[PDB]
Amino acid sequence: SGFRKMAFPSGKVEGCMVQVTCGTTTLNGLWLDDVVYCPRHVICNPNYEDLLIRKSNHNFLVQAGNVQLRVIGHSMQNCVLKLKVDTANPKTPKYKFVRIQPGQTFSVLACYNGSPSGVYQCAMRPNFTIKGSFLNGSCGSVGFNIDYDCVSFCYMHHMELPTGVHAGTDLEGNFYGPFVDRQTAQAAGTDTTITVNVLAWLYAAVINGDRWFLNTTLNDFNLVAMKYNYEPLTQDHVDILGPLSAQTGIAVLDMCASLKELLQTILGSALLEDEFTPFDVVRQCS
Amino acid sequence: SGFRKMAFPSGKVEGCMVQVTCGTTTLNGLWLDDVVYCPRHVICTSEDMLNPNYEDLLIRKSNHNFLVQAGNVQLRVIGHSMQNCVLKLKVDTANPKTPKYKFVRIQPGQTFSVLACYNGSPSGVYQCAMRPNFTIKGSFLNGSCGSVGFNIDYDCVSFCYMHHMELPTGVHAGTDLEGNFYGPFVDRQTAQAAGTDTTITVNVLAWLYAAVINGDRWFLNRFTTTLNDFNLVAMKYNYEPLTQDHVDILGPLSAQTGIAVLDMCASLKELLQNGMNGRTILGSALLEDEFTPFDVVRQC
Ligand SMILES: CC(=O)N1CCNC(=O)[C@H]1CC(=O)Nc1cccc(Cl)c1
Ligand SMILES: CC(=O)N1CCNC(=O)[C@H]1CC(=O)Nc1cccc(Cl)c1
Image (cartoon, rainbow over all chains, first blue to last red; front, side, top):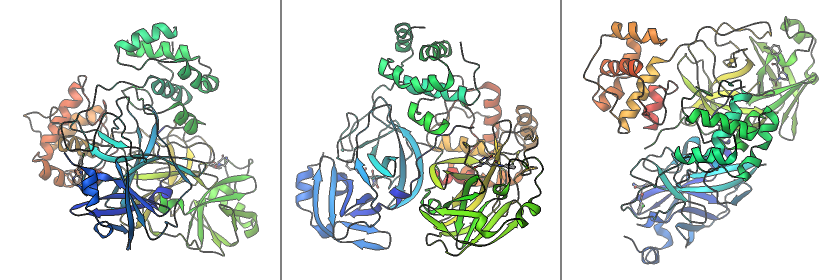
């Protein structure tokens, strides 16, 4: 029994974290094969082509624990700097670079100047920010999921927005959300609540004994959801919640009706949590 | 900025997780140097869940009765002994991945990270607090026995917890690595239940300091309070008594924010009195108590 904001074990990613210094900026890098990946703002209204063109390879200090790596080439892909080094990481996991959707979750290994300090579980918000926890020096920390010993890297941290939330890119350097790597007047848009994750979480509650909220149509549920700032529930979502209806014996629309009543504690919270995907609930409540 | 129930990186502990099988009972084990540690109830059968005699059960065992596996590798057991509720299996091979480590026993209100494992395979990591009633509100399924809890000082892992059982209320009970249970619990499957739990007062106060550090002061007021008046009120909300030791511990957070501990206590009294009024503190509508003053400083 029990239910927790549980992160993936982090050892496979810990073995890939290095420290990257350029000039007066130090941040984190991800060392896979013979390439270190880090935010391109390590070289800083900037002109990133001119900034990189004037850099030589010995202007990048890559410190892998107690061993300095020799940079033998530097390139750039979208917002990410790619540093080629003289040695391949012997600890490189089976990995792929993926890009995730809002509503999907991933684990974040917060590192500070190369050294992992803590791991936690996040969701990509509908406004493409993440409500994480990052202090100075945490730029370049990565987010990931693990599936049968393959690490799917989905996020690299770049910056904090003035509302205390965080913005970054995938590992190909493409930003999540309408953000740019300039220290300028940027702000998150109006957020919304992830309906399918709330419903999956309610399913976790009945699996773990909380049933006091149990009691519609998809069309009437969505009419109230739009007034409570909830994402519209699609049939894709309804089908995805199928396995939880099958395990708990509660139709998706019945759970929607219960959610409607709640909008008009569970699993230890006074708020309707929405950072657990249907997959997360099953993996943990198997 | 931001604030999460952040766990320690788990790689140093993942490299120590193994699978221990005795008869048809399988659980997880902790492999450090040439010793595998696991709950002693691995040697129980279906006939003696209720009143097992562990001394008698163990003397009937040979080393080859214990099947221990590190991934694909079977480890050779060359000896076995018992220390309280933990079984210690000596093996022919020392763990090449042994981190620097200590065995520690934590106090209630202290936090640690749990690496949840099944069949020696880690599946996830999360953050726990030792409740005043000596249980933890974890997330464990069948097969999770032997999973361990820990903290990391720098490169040294302090192991403080090994999981043994789930109580009828849903909470979880276990031992330190000496095999001594946290709380009045025994590794028998007779009816046991946790005592009345309470809220960890010093942790709520630390967390209110964290909220101030991250920019929120709306819950403060112009009042102060004596320590005893505070406890007289807080205990009516089922809070743990706040001791001068706790007040001393909150010192660094008080100095950092300029808010005296007892002034923050006065705020807590009002929050208990009034509620959130539709607001949140660090993203929660409840008063969180699973962050120690040391956790707050480290994350802030
Ligand atoms: C993470 C870290 O170690 N640091 C150094 C100290 N301060 C910081 O802000 C960061 C660097 C940073 O964010 N730079 C930047 C530059 C150009 C545009 C944008 Cl968006 C960001
Ligand atoms: C956790 C785990 O992996 N398993 C193996 C499969 N089945 C289980 O029951 C457990 C072991 C267990 O809890 N047994 C037990 C026996 C006597 C007293 C007490 Cl307290 C507990």
